[PDB]
Image (cartoon, rainbow over all chains, first blue to last red; front, top):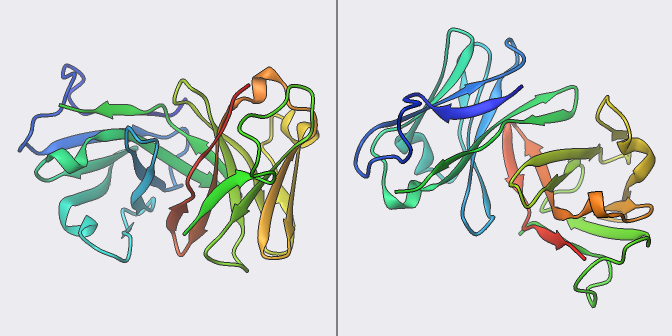
Length: 112
Length: 112
C-alpha cells in the first residue's frame, strides 16, 4: 500500500536548515504522483506532480519550484526540500490519480 | 476561492441517519472535482469524481457508489450521503485537477 516517508527512516523530525528528502512508494509505477503538504490547520497544499518519466509540474504562483525538487528514483518518487524552514512544516502525502480515481499514501509528519 | 460546505449553512453537525448534502464551489466550472473524506486519523479517502457534465467515477471496491451521490447543480458540485452513519464522519474536501496542478477547498468537518 502507498506510503510517504523520510528517506532516512531513522529520523523522527526534520532539521531546520537541512535538505529534506522524502520518498513516496506507489502501488503503481508508470503512473506519476503528486506531493502535497497539509498544515496543522488541516489546510492542504499542492507541491508538485511527478510523471513516470520524471517530468515535473509545479503550481503557477511560484516560490515552490525553487524550494522543492521532484524526481522518480528507480520505482519510488522523491521530494527534496532544499533548505527545510519553518514554513515547510506539515504532513506530507503522495497522491496517485489513475482513471479518475485517487489513491492516497499514509502521511509523513514533518515538524521540528 | 474553493470551499466545501454543508448545503444547510445553518447546521454545525450532520444528523445520524439523515441524508447529508454538501456543496463544493469551484473556482472553475467545466472542470470536474473529486470529493474526499479525511478521518480524524488524518487518513484520506476518495469518494467520487464529478465531471463538468455530471459524470461520476467511484472507487472500484464499492460500498461507495451506493452510499454517496455526486452531481453538478448549476455551477456548484454536490455530494449527498444517503443515510449519514458513524463511518461517514470526517472532514470533507473538494479537489480540482487542472493541467496536472491540484487545487483544494477548505474542509467541512462532519462529526456528530
